[PDB]
Image: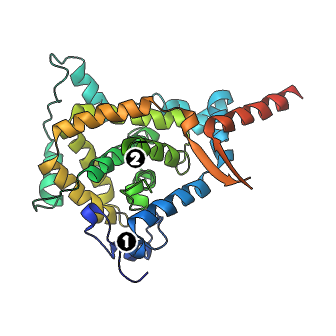
C-alpha cells in the first residue's frame, strides 16, 4: 500500500480527498482513498453497504407508508414526497405535451445564471477521453442522486442537499466508477436503490423507483436538459465549504467534458436502456447480507415478515 491510487474524472486526481477528510468531509466513505485500487473500492463499498443497511429502519418506513395513522404520515412526509415532480421534469413534460416531433430533443435556452455559471466556474480545457462508458454511467448515477434529493426536499436547497446526493452516488462516496468486481446500467440502478434504502432520511423502494423514473425523462429531454441538471448538481457542491472537493475531482470535468463532448445518441440509448433495466427489476432483486450466522434476504421478504409480526400483534 505504498503507490498512490488515482481517482475521480478519468483517474486524474489524488491527495484532495484525504486532505478533505481532515476538514470534515463526511461524504467520503473510503478508509484509505489514496491507496485503494478501483477493484478494492467495489469490494469495500459492497461490504459497507451491507453493514449500513438497517432492516428495522427499512421495514419501519414501509409500515409507516402502508399502515401509519395521519400523525405518523404527517411527520414522516412519504406521501407528500411521492406526489412531488421536480422542476426539471415539469419543464420536459410541459414541452413534450405540445411537441409535434416527440422523438426529437427538447430545445433549451440556458438562463443568464446558467450561462454565468458555465463561463465562471467550469474548466475551459479541451478533452480527449477515450474511455467514455464510466462517464455516462457516472451521469446516470448522479442524475439519480440529484432527482432523489429534489424529491426528498420538494425542490428546496437545504443543509443536507449535497450530503444526500453524495451518499447516493457510488462515484462520489466511494470514488467508484467501476461498480462491478447484469449490465453495468442495471448494476448502477440496483446500486442507487440499495444506497437510497441505506443512507437517506426517507428509505422507501417506491421513492427510489420514482427517482429512477424521473431520470429516464430527464435523459429523454436530451443533452441540454442533462446539462441543466448537471449545472444544478455542480452549483450545490460548488459553494459547500467542505464538499466542493467533489466538483474539483469529478463534477467540474464531468460537466465541462459532457458539454463539449456529450453525444445525443448515447444519451437517448442510455434513456431507453436504463428504462428497460429499471422495468426488469422488482423488490426481489434488492438483497442485503448480514449476521442474523449469515443470511441473505430480499426487501420483499423483510416487508412480509414485518407485516406478519404486525398482523399477529394487532390480533392479540
Does 97 sit left or right of 215 as displayed? left
Residue 258's x, y, as percent? 19, 49
User: Above or below — where is 13 with respect to 81?
Assistant: below
Which residue lies at the image location 33% right of the left edge and 76% below the top edge? 15
Q: Earlier in the sequence, mark 1 or mark 2?
A: 1
Which residue lies at the image location 47% right of the left edge and 65% below the top edge? 26
Q: Can you name the residue that lies furthest to the right here? A: 316
Does 167 sit left or right of 202 as displayed? left
Which quadrant is home to the C terminus?
A: top right
Residue 13 is drawn in which quadrant? bottom left
Residue pointed to by mark 1: 17
Residue 95's x, y, as percent? 21, 24
User: Number of labelled discs?
Assistant: 2
Residue pointed to by mark 2: 145
| CA gap, disc 1 and disc 2 | 20 Å
Secondary structure found at label 1: helix
Residue 256's x, y, as percent? 17, 55
Which residue lies at the image location 43% right of the left edge and 45% below the top edge? 187
Secondary structure found at label 2: helix
Q: Are discs 1 and 2 less than 8 Å apart at CB?
A: no
Which quadrant is home to the N terminus?
A: bottom left
**Number of other residues with Cα within 10 Å of mark 1, as a class: few under 14, some 14 to 19, many 20 or more:** many
Work out whether residue 256 can be spotted. Answer: yes
User: Above or below — where is 150 with respect to 30?
Assistant: above
Amino acid at each position: 500500500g505504498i503507490l498512490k491510487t488515482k481517482y475521480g474524472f478519468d483517474n486524474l486526481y489524488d491527495t484532495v480527498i484525504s486532505v478533505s477528510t481532515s476538514n470534515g468531509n463526511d461524504i467520503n466513505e473510503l478508509d484509505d482513498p489514496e491507496h485503494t485500487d478501483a477493484n478494492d473500492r467495489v469490494i469495500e463499498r459492497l461490504r459497507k453497504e451491507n453493514l449500513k443497511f438497517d432492516p428495522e429502519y427499512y421495514v419501519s418506513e414501509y409500515m409507516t407508508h402502508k399502515y401509519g395513522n395521519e400523525e405518523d404520515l404527517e411527520i414522516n412526509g412519504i406521501k407528500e414526497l411521492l406526489k412531488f415532480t421536480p422542476s426539471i421534469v415539469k419543464q420536459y413534460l410541459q414541452w413534450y405535451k405540445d411537441s409535434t416531433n416527440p422523438n426529437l430533443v427538447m430545445p433549451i435556452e440556458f438562463t443568464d445564471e446558467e450561462q454565468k455559471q458555465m463561463q465562471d466556474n467550469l474548466p475551459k480545457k479541451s478533452y480527449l477521453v477515450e474511455d467514455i462508458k464510466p462517464l455516462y454511467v457516472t451521469i446516470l448515477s448522479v442524475l439519480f442522486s440529484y432527482v432523489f434529493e429534489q424529491i426528498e426536499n420538494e425542490g428546496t436547497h437545504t443543509t443536507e442537499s449535497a450530503w444526500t446526493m453524495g451518499k447516493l452516488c457510488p462515484q462520489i462516496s466511494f470514488l467508484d466508477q467501476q461498480l462491478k468486481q447484469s449490465s453495468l446500467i442495471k448494476i448502477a440502478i440496483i446500486t442507487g436503490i440499495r444506497r437510497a434504502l441505506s443512507y437517506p432520511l426517507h428509505r422507501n423502494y417506491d421513492l427510489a423507483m420514482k427517482a429512477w423514473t424521473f431520470v429516464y425523462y430527464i435523459l429523454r429531454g436530451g443533452k441540454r436538459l442533462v446539462i441543466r441538471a448537471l449545472l444544478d448538481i455542480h452549483e450545490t457542491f460548488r459553494f459547500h465549504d467542505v464538499y466542493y472537493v467533489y466538483d474539483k475531482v469529478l463534477l467540474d470535468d464531468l460537466t465541462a467534458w459532457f458539454i463539449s463532448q456529450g453525444s445525443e445518441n448515447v444519451i437517448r440509448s442510455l434513456a431507453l436502456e436504463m428504462r428497460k433495466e429499471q422495468e426488469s427489476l422488482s423488490k426481489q432483486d434488492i438483497e442485503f447480507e448480514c449476521i442474523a450466522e449469515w443470511e441473505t434476504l430480499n426487501i420483499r421478504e423483510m416487508e412480509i415478515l414485518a407485516e406478519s409480526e404486525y398482523r399477529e400483534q394487532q390480533q392479540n
